[PDB]
Image 1: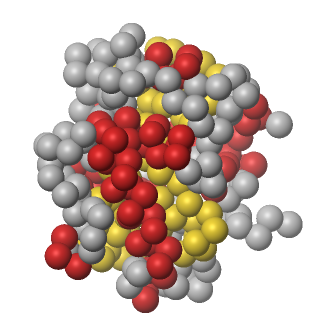
Image 2 (image 1 turned 60 degrees about the vertical axis):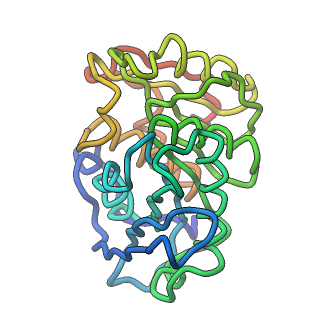
Length: 258
C-alpha cells in the first residue's frame, strides 16, 4: 500500500471544488515570527492523519488574501498550507525565496500545536504567484529535498534555474506583466532535461488568473502536489495524455507518467 494516500478515488470534477477534508485556519501575525511576514495556515481538521505541507508566496504588492481560495482548496484535498505575507509587500523574487525557506522551517519546527499535529515534516513543497513564482523557482534550486514546485504566472529576471525538484509551471496566454514568451516558457525550457517538468498555458487568461477560483489551476496544482508529495499515482491520469479545452498549450518531458 501507499501510506501517504488520502481521500477517495479522484474525478476531474471533484478537483474543481473544495475537497473532502474540513479546513481550519490559523492567522500568523508578523510579530510572532522572524524571517517572513506571517500569513495564514489552512489545514485539515476532524482527522487523525498527517499530511504533506506547502508554503505559498503571493506576488508584488499583494497579500496572502490574493491566494486564499487556493490555500483553502489545497488544504481541503489533504495538505497543510501556509500562505505567507512578506516582510515588505515590495520584496523581490529572491527575497521571496528566502521567506519561503523561513516559512517551511517554521512549519516544521515552531508552528502551532494543532497545525504541527497534522504535518509530516518530511514531505514539503512550494508554490507561488508572479514574483512569488520566481521565488518558487529559486528555492527549488536551493533546496532539492522539496517534493514539488508550482510557479503560477511566474516572473523573474533570471531565466535559468538548476533544480531537480519536479516543476509544473502555469502560464497565462494574455499575460502582459510576466509575458509567457519572456518568463514562463523560458523557465520551462531552461530547466534541466532530466527534471520532471510540465508547462500548462491557460487560454486567453491574464496575469491575475491565479487570484480567484480557477478550475484549471485547481486541477493541475492539486494533481502535481498529490503525485509528488504523496506519491499518489492515482493523480497521474490528470497529468498524462491530457486534452483540456481550458488550455491552449501543454508541454512535458513525461517523466512523471511512469
